[PDB]
Amino acid sequence: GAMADIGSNIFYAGDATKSNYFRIPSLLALDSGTVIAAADARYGGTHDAKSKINTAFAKSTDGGKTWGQPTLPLKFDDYVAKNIDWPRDSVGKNVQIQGSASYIDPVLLEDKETHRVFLFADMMPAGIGSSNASVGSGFKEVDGKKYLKLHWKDDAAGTYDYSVRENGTIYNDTTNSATEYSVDGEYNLYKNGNAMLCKQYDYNFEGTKLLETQTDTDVNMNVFYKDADFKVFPTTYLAMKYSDDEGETWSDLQIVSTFKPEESKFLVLGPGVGKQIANGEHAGRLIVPLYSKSSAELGFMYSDDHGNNWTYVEADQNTGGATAEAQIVEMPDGSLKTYLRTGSGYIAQVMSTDGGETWSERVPLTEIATTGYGTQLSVINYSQPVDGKPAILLSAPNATNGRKNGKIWIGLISETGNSGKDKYSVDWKYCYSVDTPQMGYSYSCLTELPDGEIGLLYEKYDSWSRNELHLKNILKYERFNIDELKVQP
Ligand SMILES: CC(=O)N[C@H]1[C@H]([C@H](O)[C@H](O)CO)OC(C(=O)O)=C[C@@H]1O
């Protein structure tokens, strides 16, 4: 590493998370000027769920120069957290953990009006990922009210005759009566006040066979575990916790996806950051991007009451479930521009003028090359004029073959003198090269730091490639002043 690369790891193999791998960066400068970050702690190599993944978290007091020890605010204990070197061979490289619960794909958001920070992540029951989730919400309605549904072990497959109700009281819905079972605030199970338990799994390889085997370590039976007496419906959930103390402590787990459409296979987070509206009618609205295999592809969830309640909105009617990972910026009036990945070989743009309730048709973004499968991007507002215009920054790879050639772009915003969603034009005038064209570059998250420097946490390899799986120390942190970035190639 060069002098300039010292301090370019936040999460790394050997830190406190006990993970050898990390993916999916999230980076956010708070209003106070503290800076926080989050990423997947991918234990079982860099595979997506299904796997064993927890959400990692760290922060910087010194404006993002330096980072504290990492924490695990969203974590499951059904399989142990350990440092294991995943095989990289033609056969083994493909092997993933079949039986663990996971948190995956974080989003960080701050309510600046209340100084509350929210952490969201997809919540996967045991052995589930987006690809093998079932169709359904995971909740039932009982006398008009939504309750998380549960399968008792000795009931017929696909039979969910129970529900978590007030106080975590588990009810039998056939007779509508409380049982002796309940869940606590962690969704761990109890029988007549007594903690239920089960044996934690280990995983070790013998050659290219992955051996997932019980140990003699008791952990709390959780409804998200493979070996629980009561089990949630095996679809994708959204989880959130909040902190008022900049991530020093976290609130209780919230399964917020009560709005998951019954017709959807998965509904998951567009990783990166969310947005608080600063200007206009809907100023103060909190909004978080989502995408799904459902009635719609792109969606959002928003709160007009500082995080207590969340409303789901569909931005299109595509049923094909392409990976429409999005990030959102604000126009100076306060309308929203969203930039998103697609599976159609380009990055797309959409506008909303009603605070994200409705959205315009997708518009391709010509200026940036990408692959057919696409990659996640990061877009943000910059607080300062740039050549005397309001500006945004976008980070994304810039190649048609592979995830590589990452750029940071500066877009300059103009009024076109037209009306509505067309009020504004973005001029992508600057294009900064992060490394070289053949260097790998995948997911990324920008933030503007306190001093007005631009921070970047990114995947410095190609995370799609089947030949770059299970690499360590690929998650890189760099800082730039705004003049560095003003390049015109
Ligand atoms: C929830 C989940 O799996 N998210 C993953 C997403 C997904 O795998 C798929 O592309 C669409 O269903 O893709 C990628 C990726 O590197 O492309 C990373 C995410 O971690």
Image (cartoon, helix red, strand yellow):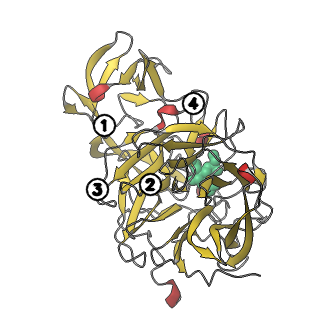
- Residue under label 1, please give it: 188
Q: Which mark is residue 249?
A: 3
* Residue nearer the viewer, 380 or 464: 380
Residue 471 horizontal/vertical position (percent) = 56, 67
Q: Residue at x 68, y 50 (%)?
A: 351
Q: Which mark is residue 207?
A: none
Disc 3 marks a residue whose amino acid type is Thr
Q: Specify the quadrant that holds the C terminus.
A: bottom right
Using the numbered discs, state the Cα–Cα distance from disc 4 to disc 1 in whole angstroms: 25 Å
Disc 4 marks a residue whose amino acid type is Pro
Using the numbered discs, state the Cα–Cα distance from disc 3 to disc 1 in whole angstroms: 20 Å
Q: Residue at x 34, y 37 (%)?
A: 222
Q: Could one spot residue 100 in this view of the protein? A: no
Cβ atoms at labels 4 and 2 below 8 Å apart: no
Q: Residue at x 67, y 81 (%)?
A: 486
Q: Nearer the viewer, mark 2 or mark 3?
A: 3
Disc 1 marks a residue whose amino acid type is Asn
- Residue under label 4, please give it: 261
Residue 110 appears in which quarter of the rendering?
bottom left
Q: On the rendered structure, is 335 left or right of 99?
A: right
- Residue under label 2, please give it: 204
> Around disc 3, counting alpha carbons within 10 Å, would you say few (fewer than 14), some (14 to 19), or many (20 or more)?
few
Using the numbered discs, state the Cα–Cα distance from disc 4 to disc 2 in whole angstroms: 38 Å
| Mark found first going from the N terminus, 4 or 2 | 2
Using the numbered discs, state the Cα–Cα distance from disc 4 to disc 3 in whole angstroms: 32 Å
Disc 2 marks a residue whose amino acid type is Asn
* Residue nearer the viewer, 101 or 270: 270
Above or below residue 296? Residue 392 is below
Using the numbered discs, state the Cα–Cα distance from disc 1 to disc 2 in whole angstroms: 26 Å
User: Circle 3 sits in a helix, a strand or a loop, which is it?
Assistant: loop
User: Circle 1 sits in a helix, a strand or a loop, which is it?
Assistant: loop
| Mark found first going from the N terminus, 4 or 3 | 3
